[PDB]
Image (cartoon, coloured by chain):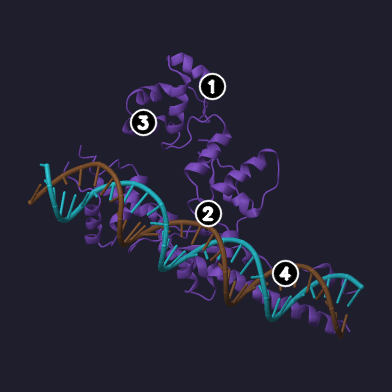
Chain colours: A purple, B cyan, C brown
Amino acid sequence: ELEELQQNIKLELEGKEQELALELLNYLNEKGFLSKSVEEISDVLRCSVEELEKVRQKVLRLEPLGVCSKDVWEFLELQIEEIYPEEEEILKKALRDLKRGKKLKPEIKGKLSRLRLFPSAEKVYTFAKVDAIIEEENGEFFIYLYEDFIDIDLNEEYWELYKNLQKELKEAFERYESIRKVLDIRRRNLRKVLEKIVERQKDFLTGKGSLKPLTLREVSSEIGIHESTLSRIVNSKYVKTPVGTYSLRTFFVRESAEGLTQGELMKLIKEIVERKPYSDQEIANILKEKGFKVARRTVAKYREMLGIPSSRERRI
DNA sequence: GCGAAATTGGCACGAAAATTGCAATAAATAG
DNA sequence: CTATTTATTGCAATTTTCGTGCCAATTTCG
């Protein structure tokens, strides 16, 4: 809630920014955004509009994200910049044409489902259709498929053919049983994927765990499908889980060293930091003895993403 | 202090991988 | 029944991302 934001405000903010931020949000709709403009917010606290508009852009950058922003679009625009920069080019493009009105591709609609409109379960898009489902009790681990309920829809030709009939139904069943078999292999491939990914990702779907690395090259060499055909499965197929409904491409990550997802790795560096302490190359030595071989330079980049002004400057 | 080893960041290049365009084959519809 | 264009699998090329290596710039220790 607000208590969560106020406590994080003091960590990275000092001076007027901390004094301003606490008094800065007394203006909001329970949807999370303020009814007042920066024009009015400046005159009340006896501060200029250069200070307020400067700090507000930083305040949304602290979890929980996107608090003060007035527009839904600023919240969505900040979500794409701050969260999904890899696809940020495409995602921002989906918002503009949507405002003027427009249609959306099944992939573009699903890509936008990850965004949230405003701060519990509010989300912009929820799928009417889901291409599979997965769940676990403490009991493990159920995969429904979708097409398991689906069979060839008899077209007008078969129904009207009753208008050498013994041979006619033969041919219709010949074509049908052939396509019914290929559709079984197409859905059987779905079962092969999830049964494989569940082994790694068990923690992620259930609970406390965080995403474990998975490579298409790793998976596509595990079973008959090639990575080229596997890549279009993950993009076009969506799944429901105990925690959320994800693109199926969200379960594939890249690994550094013996692990590791970039997230799990980032937390380790932040944990090791928890005058004397090691600067950079020294900290890579802790992990190499920790079982994970790393590079001296690589810890520097992850030291920049999460706040570490310096391991040296934390000494002074 | 002076010199040598270093912390840190940059420009980037390379490797491992993923996505999209291309072509070949199996298929369906129309003439 | 044959031909054309229709879609899916497999292959190749390109772009995509992420790590790491070295050198330069500022620093610390012997």
- Dot 2: few (<14), some (14–19), or many (≥20) neighbours within 10 Å? some
* Callout 2 touching callout 1 (CB < 8 Å): no
Do the dots labelled 2 and 4 sit on one chain?
Answer: yes
Residue at (53% x, 26% y) in the render: A29
Q: Picture coordinates of residue A138 (x, y %)?
A: 41, 58
Residue at (60% x, 47% y) in the render: A126
Q: Label 4 vs label 1: CA separation?
A: 58 Å
Residue at (47% x, 60% y) in the render: A252
The residue that mark 3 highlights is: A9
The residue that mark 2 highlights is: A246
* Closer to us: A148 or A287: A287
Residue at (54% x, 68% y) in the render: A191
Mark 2 belongs to chain: A
Pair 2/1: label in front: 1
* Closer to us: A75 or A147: A75
Residue A152 disc label: 4
Q: Describe the element under mark 4 as helix, strand or loop.
A: loop
Amino acid tagged 2: Tyr
Amino acid tagged 1: Ser
Q: Label 2 vs label 3: CA separation?
A: 31 Å
Q: Label 2 vs label 1: CA separation?
A: 36 Å
Q: Along the polypeptide, which appears first: circle 2 or circle 1?
A: 1
Mark 3 belongs to chain: A
The quadrant of the rendering that contains the C terminus of chain A is: top left
